[PDB]
Length: 110
Length: 126
Length: 52
Ligand SMILES: *[C@@H]1O[C@H](CO)[C@@H](O[C@@H]2O[C@H](CO)[C@@H](O[C@@H]3O[C@H](CO[C@H]4O[C@H](CO[C@H]5O[C@H](CO)[C@@H](O)[C@H](O)[C@@H]5O)[C@@H](O)[C@H](O[C@H]5O[C@H](CO)[C@@H](O)[C@H](O)[C@@H]5O)[C@@H]4O)[C@@H](O)[C@H](O[C@H]4O[C@H](CO)[C@@H](O)[C@H](O)[C@@H]4O[C@H]4O[C@H](CO)[C@@H](O)[C@H](O)[C@@H]4O)[C@@H]3O)[C@H](O)[C@H]2NC(C)=O)[C@H](O)[C@H]1NC(C)=O
Ligand SMILES: *[C@@H]1O[C@H](CO)[C@@H](O[C@@H]2O[C@H](CO)[C@@H](O[C@@H]3O[C@H](CO)[C@@H](O)[C@H](O)[C@@H]3O)[C@H](O)[C@H]2NC(C)=O)[C@H](O)[C@H]1NC(C)=O
Ligand SMILES: *[C@@H]1O[C@H](CO)[C@@H](O)[C@H](O)[C@H]1NC(C)=O
Image (tube, rainbow over the protein chains, first blue to last red):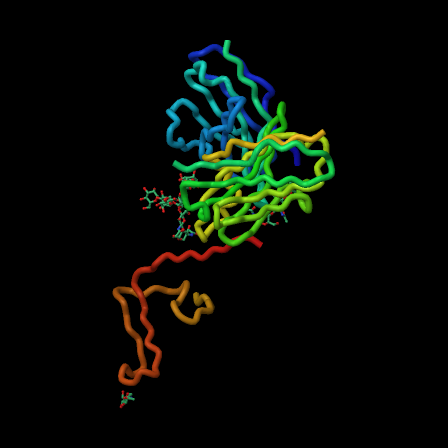
């Protein structure tokens, strides 16, 4: 019962779409559709990015597209700028009222 | 506007206990859950159990049972977290986060929708 | 086909009526006889529970 899988780091140029995904056990992500993503700049508290697999929270523009397929939860990044240098985190329901968080991604802007 | 404030940064020694108090202001906090997360500097987040400010039910994650207690105080709108038996790798930052909505009809405890967060507190040991 | 459901009030799964709401009773003069109302259209009902 360890953390959910996540790639170590991502990189890319501004202006295009960047894909990130979490895979896990079907008892965690494959059985329940309660998966959310988090963005954390280093220095203060993170901010909520997405409620469901896809329904937008208030104060966030349509730039962050989420989806779920099988056991893969994917977030795609459209239109990168300098305000994206942060960390991206999975979290999901796991049964027995437990929440499992993801591993962590480092994003560098080229 | 609602706010979540915490205690100061704590320095400790292994084999002790630590109190962290999270205070919520600006809204009726008894209708919303309260989750706790921790993060060592350099690695990811992980999750402890929630507290329900209506009745007093409490869950916990694994490797925390018999080690951590959570307490309400509804008079001044705050939640206490006691963590005992500290060891060397517990140096981290702690955040208290608002959970779902208690609605008297569904188990909304495990809905990972943390929208408002505290500033976090830094607890270190030597 | 008869479904042997058990219900005190508010009859569950069963055969509907044909044309309209129909009243069945023994006398309709004294108040000790249970009057049965038979409906033409059904109403959905759900009943759930938390975990054990
Ligand atoms: C059997 O039937 C019963 C019938 O009752 C069913 O029970 C009902 O079940 C549904 C869902 O299954 C519940 O709905 C949920 O309600 C919550 C609460 O929302 C209310 O409060 C909002 C907050 O405002 C109050 O609180 C502040 C706090 O200070 C006060 O200051 C205010 O003055 C208020 O008192 C309020 O904004 C809400 O308004 C919404 O609804 C009205 C209805 O008429 C609309 O007009 C509004 O425009 C607005 O839409 C409401 O009054 C909702 O918040 C829940 O939605 C959340 O969860 C969804 C699922 O994830 C999610 O998709 C939503 O986006 C939403 O997300 C929320 O997530 C976090 C929760 O903390 C936060 O980030 C944030 O708050 C965000 O909003 C949900 O809709 C009913 O409450 C419940 N009935 C009762 C009586 O409790 C039962 O399910 C049936 N059983 C079956 C079918 O088995
Ligand atoms: C309602 O209560 C039941 C009580 O059984 C919950 O079922 C239990 O859910 C947990 C979720 O973690 C299961 O644990 C998993 O077991 C598999 C078995 O191989 C393991 O591989 C996983 O790593 C994990 O430990 C547990 O087995 C399961 N109980 C049984 C008897 O199967 C259920 O989840 C509760 N409902 C909700 C919505 O949480
Ligand atoms: C029951 O019905 C009969 C005839 O249908 C009638 O004579 C009798 O008075 C009724 N009972 C009462 C209590 O009125």
